[PDB]
Image (cartoon, rainbow, N blue to C red):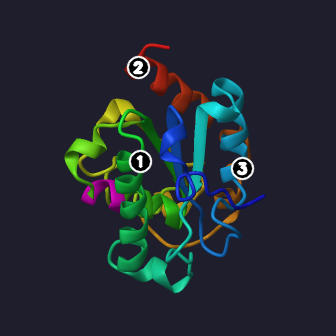
Amino acid sequence: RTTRDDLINGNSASCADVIFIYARGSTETGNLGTLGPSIASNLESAFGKDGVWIQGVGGAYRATLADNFLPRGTSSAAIREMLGLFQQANTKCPDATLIAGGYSQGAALAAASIEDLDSAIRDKIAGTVLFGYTKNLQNRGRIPNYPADRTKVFCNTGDLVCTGSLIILAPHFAYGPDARGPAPEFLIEKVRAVRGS
């Protein structure tokens, strides 16, 4: 339901052509949360069940509230977790195109992990989508070390976390529409431009 593990248990002899690594937000259940499943259903329709592997960031990432106050908007531990998954994907399936996404704290996590990622693997990521990015102001609407034409941030009007504060108002919980449509569509568009399809 809110937990998908296709990379971790993924059989190398049956590699997906695409792999989606996603990070939930504070307090959210499973390793996908409330938005994760929405994007996934879309990826499976465009590519097929056998076409994509959906992987959430669980393990050591335990979307804690207090960790929003840490230097990089997340824990040192969580960053290694997500970083670890990228390396694993590149290992089991070196020909698979990679894509990623994150929400609130997971948005911060995605930014930090891809920033610390080995450049050769980082080039494999066709696209990344971020919702209610907590480090938007600070990181100037971008992901450190990642290209503009591959990044897509969603920051509703009124959401102060995008402005640079940690005040959580109502707009922060309104990314459902985005996740059901513009998010997966941008990712799918990205996968086909870099491969052929």
Magenta-drawn segment: 112-116
Locate the N terminus and report the quarter of the image it occupies. Answer: bottom right
Residue found at x 36% / y 70%:
80
Q: Position of residue 82 (x, y in %)?
A: 42, 63
Question: Which mark identifies residue 195?
Answer: 2
Q: Position of residue 190 (x, y in %)?
A: 46, 26
Q: Earlier in the sequence, mark 1 or mark 3?
A: 3
Residue type for callout 2: Arg
Q: Earlier in the sequence, mark 1 or mark 2?
A: 1
Depicted 101 relative to depicted 135: above or below:
above
Of labels 2 and 3, the one closer to you: 2
Q: Nearer the viewer, residue 5 or 99?
A: 5
Say few, some or many: other residues with alpha carbon within 10 Å of mark 2 (under 14 / 14 to 19 / 20 or more): few
Q: Position of residue 3 (x, y in %)?
A: 69, 61
Residue type for callout 3: Pro
The reply to whether callout 1 and callout 3 are in contact (CB within 8 Å) is no
Q: Earlier in the sequence, mark 2 or mark 3?
A: 3
* Secondary-structure class at tag 3: helix
Question: Which mark identifies residue 92?
Answer: 1
- Counting every numbered tag in the picture gives 3
Looking at the image, which residue sits at the far bottom? Answer: 66
Asked whether residue 59 is drawn in magenta, I would say no
Q: CA gap, disc 1 to disc 3?
A: 24 Å
Residue found at x 71% / y 53%:
174
Q: CA gap, disc 1 to disc 2?
A: 19 Å
- Say whether residue 111 is visible: yes
Q: CA gap, disc 2 to disc 3?
A: 25 Å
Residue found at x 51% / y 67%:
105
Question: Which mark identifies residue 37?
Answer: 3
Depicted 98 relative to depicted 51: above or below:
below
